[PDB]
Image (cartoon, rainbow over all chains, first blue to last red; front, side, top):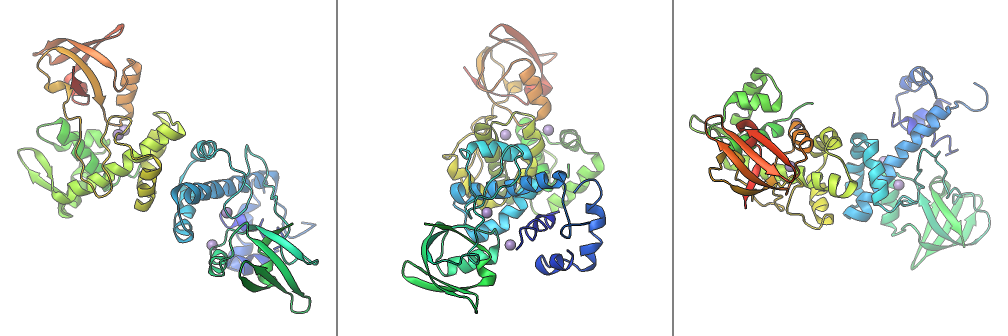
Length: 204
Length: 215
Ligand SMILES: [Mn+2]
Ligand SMILES: [Mn+2]
Ligand SMILES: [Mn+2]
Ligand SMILES: [Mn+2]
C-alpha cells in the first residue's frame, strides 16, 4: 500500500533485493506480496512494470501527502516532528473530496514545502526538479530546490541549517571519494554521494 | 460507525438540555444502538467518573464530564466551521466525514485550527464554541416546547442531526430564519408556526430539538 509508494521511488533510480534493503520490508513479504499486486492492474525491461492503473493511483497518494503538508506547515505553523506524527495519519483518514476542497483553498499551490510537485486533476506525477547533486560534474553556484519527504533527512538538513531554496556554492568535487563540498552563508559542508542522491539542486 | 464513548457523552449532554429526566430509551433511540450496548456503555462511563446516576434528572454530568464535553464540543464544532464555512461542505458530506475527523485529529491540530478560523464563536447550527481550556456554556437554551406565550421567534440553534436537518431543509427552515407562533395546542402539544409563505405544525418531539429566541 504505502510501501508500493517506494517501488516508484527506487524506480526513480534511487527487482526484489532492492525492495527489502531500501524500505526495510520482510524478505519473504517482498516476493510473496507481489502475487496480490500483480492481480487487478499494476517480465522484460527492469524488475517490475506498473500499469496506468497504478501510476495514476500513487499520484493521488503523493497528492494527499503534499497537500496536507502545505496545509500544516504554511497555515497551521507545524514543525517537522508534528508533521511526521500527524500527516501520515491524516492522509490515511481524510477523503478525496476533502483534499479537493483543500486544494482550492490553498490557492492551488504548485510545490510541496520540501519542493515536490503537486499533481492535479488526475494528472500523472511529473517532478520539475529532477537534477540531483551527485550528477553535477561542473562547478558553480546552485539553489537547493527539492528534497525527499524523509524525516531523518530533514533532521540532517535542519541540523546544518540547510533550508530549501538556499543559495549555495559548490567548491570541491572529489571524484575518488565521491564527495561534494558546498558553501552556504557562513558554513561549509561535505556531502557523501549517498546523501547527494537525495538533494535536488537548480543551476544559477 | 464505531460510536465511541465520547459520542455517548455528547448525546447525554444534549438530552439533558432537551429533557427533564434522561432515560436509557432516549439514549438508545438517539444513538441508534440497542439497549444492552447502551446500558453497558453507561456502566463504563459512570465508572470512569464522567456520569453520576440520579433518579430525578436521569443522569448527571460530573465536573470531569463537563470539562471534557467542553473540549469535545470544541473540537466537533470547530471542525464543522472549517468543513462548511471554508471547504464548502454540504450537510450530508459532513454526516459522513466530520465525526471520523473529530475522532482522529490531535488536540494541537484543533488549537491551530481555531486560530486560522479567526476565533469563531458559533457552530453553523448555532452551537457555542468554547476557547482553549474554557468550559462550555450555551447561549441558546430555550427550546420551543417550553414556550407558553404567542409571538414572533428566531430559530437560533439545532443539533447536527441528519434526519433533523433533512426535516428543516425540506420545509425550507434554516438557522436564523424568522417566524411567528400562531397556534399552541396544550392538549395535542402542537406548535403551529408561520414563516414567509409557509405554515408548519410542530409536534413536541420535534419542538424539543428546536432552540428558539423570543421576538
Ligand atoms: Mn513534501
Ligand atoms: Mn520517514
Ligand atoms: Mn453542532
Ligand atoms: Mn445523526
